[PDB]
Length: 589
Ligand SMILES: [Cl-]
Image (tube, rainbow, N blue to C red):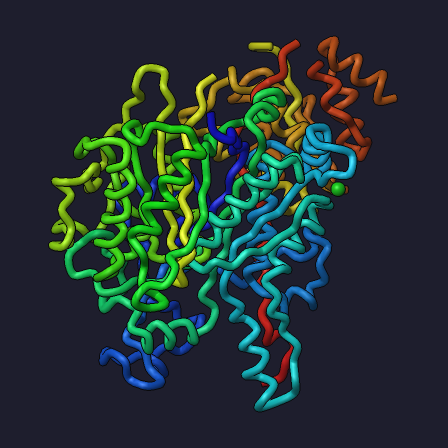
């Protein structure tokens, strides 16, 4: 049966991919997003040296990097701009990730709490937050400054990553940051699923964050020789002699499947089972254990109640290590061997070949790739493995290394089944089992839009306009779009409302608002009785309600949709202000 935990929303920010849609495009095109160290971060010429193991140097100069990790919208989160400057970028980016995930799920803060609270006991929490992270590097800058100047305070609390989200969301569930290194994100998901199953909270936000903000990490992988000579993760490829670090922030909104189905939530997939263990005493602290990996994979399978023969795809750890890669396959082989003797039926690959080793966030990026493959029914290439690692025999294995884009066909009406592994360098292992889900036309709707100020509002109109021009959208989607923007967004200061019945009309109105030109009739803008107006709107006269709402009137939009409720759909998230904050702000040179 499984623990039946539904995924009702997701957000992701990965190298070369500001959002999940872009991430899929990169994955589909087999794009390599690895680059050299951005000059803005630090002067890497002070540390680079091609000779392995040189003291005070590093032979790696590559990485999977995000763009503008110092960009943040503190006013949006009720954080003072002064506080933002000394606040760990990981906390900042996870805050923005958390919000985007709620918007993808089609939930406002208040709505999410209400939906969660109804499913658990009185004194049980509503929303839980489980974050995975392993580095506190921002802290180091403050110390480097304080020694040769005036002492500056730069906090290094990993708990803040989860705690600030809980604070912002007004969440009352468990608020936990976990560190199991590379397996952190998957460990967070594991604990989140356990909390939901146990009834500790109604919904749970689970994810991971990992940034490369300091050169120290590179001096470390250089000394320990963990870094690859070519700055690539050759997942199961020949010549892989280490990994390349990558940046990333991701999260999922988790919920018991029954509750999601009953609430008409989007369902991006279902977590059937999770498992967590440790490699024990191997021949070295950072030496992986194939038997432990096999055990955690089987444990997740048993908890999921699945038949491993049906597994269509495995998203592997695949860091591109001399010892690690063959060990991982050995672990997987031992796992499958306890159930079937079948060969070459399962696909395998790693996103790390695309975006690098995201470490504490590797699992959430991996989950994204897996869910996206199922969503589009397409298996994506795994890079840097034109010739496979000589130590690995895929011919005598359950697997076939995915090296070309290919269709992932559904067997009958049976859900596509996938597996996801993440193995911490310190020995902590994790495996997650997921499967996908199987389940007023033409009328005038009222499309609503709000943001912090006028500029952000017109920005939202533009991004929504650009989205609704894509091929997937038609006029038949208008009831879903309107519903999502009503009950799935926060009613903010600057507001925009328009009554439309066709999609091209909505696009025109959005374009007008975005460009600040003249608005049509039935459209209302504001830079910043209900019972009567809602009855009117339910009778097909929504203009007085829309105009009143734009003027600032609070509106319980749910009252409008009490035959069948429209579907929540994926719409563009809030356009955060991109102002730069760093610890050197205000400090003398
Ligand atoms: Cl609130």
